[PDB]
Length: 84
Image 1: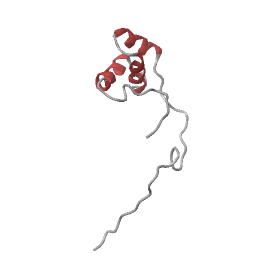
Image 2: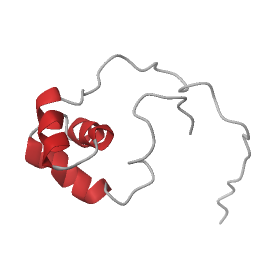
Image 3: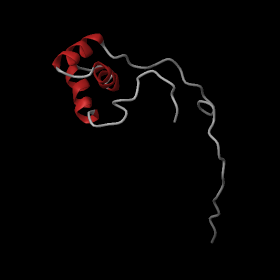
Image 4: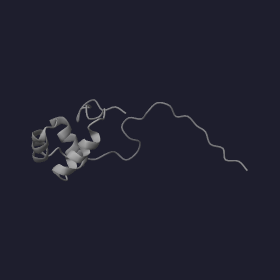
């Protein structure tokens, strides 16, 4: 028997191969953020959190924060020079 499997592509594509992305993203609710930013959190994060939770609820947003408090992304900007 034989499997055979090995190849190299190298370099990354520009955006996404086939099927382009569309406009459909959450927004750091001003209410959920204004609430978090009040609770004693970082707006930036308060934003991400909510967003991360589609601003499902202040609790959700925070919960995320409590799970994204000690993260590098928490520092990363929401809208910047994307790259990955």
